[PDB]
Image (spheres, grey):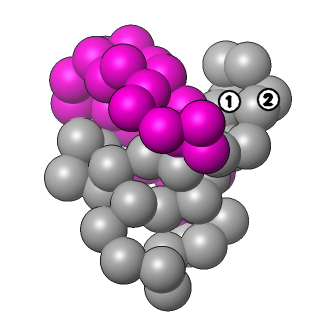
Amino acid sequence: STLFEALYDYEARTEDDLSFHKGEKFQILNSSEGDWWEARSLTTGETGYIPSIYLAPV
């Protein structure tokens, strides 16, 4: 598997979302629930959902 990094800043829109900045890295936990992946921030340690389109590998 691979870590993903944010291509752009994102502000959470739902309570299950994470907010994040460009360059923040994520461990992806689940991608089977549509475009928003469940992930863990390698900056904050928090788990939540993030838009896959906002991310790229490495």
In this view, 29 is above or below 16: below
- Taking the magenta stretch, the answer to whether it contains residue 24 is yes
Check disc 1 and report its element: helix, strand or loop. loop
Q: Residue at position x 36%, y 77% from top?
A: 34
Q: Residue 21 carries which label?
A: none
Residue 2 shown left or right of residue 58 in the figure: right
For this view, does 35 lie left or right of residue 44? left
Residue 2 x %, y %: 50, 61
Q: Quadrant of the N terminus?
A: bottom right
Disc 1 and disc 2: Cα gap in Å? Answer: 6 Å
Q: Is mark 2 on a helix, strand or loop?
A: loop
User: Disc 1 vs disc 2: which is toward the camera?
Assistant: 2
Number of labelled discs? 2
Contact, mark 1 vs mark 2 (Cβ under 8 Å): yes
x and y, in percent, of residue 8 in the image: 21, 23
Would residue 27 appear left or right of 19 to someone viewing this image? right
Corner quadrant of residue 5: top left
Q: Which residue is the site of mark 2?
A: 45
Highlighted magenta segment, given as a residue range = 2-28
Q: Which of 6 and 3 is in front in this view?
A: 6
Q: Circle 1 is placed at which residue position? A: 42
The one nearer the camera, 6 or 11, is 11
For the stretch drawn in magenta, what is the main secondary structure? Answer: loop
Above or below for 2 versus 25: below
Q: Does the magenta stretch include residue 56?
A: no
Residue type at tag 1: Leu
Q: Residue at x 79, y 29 (%)?
A: 45
In this view of the protein, which residue sits in the foreground, 7 or 12?
A: 12
Q: Can residue 13 be seen in this view?
A: yes
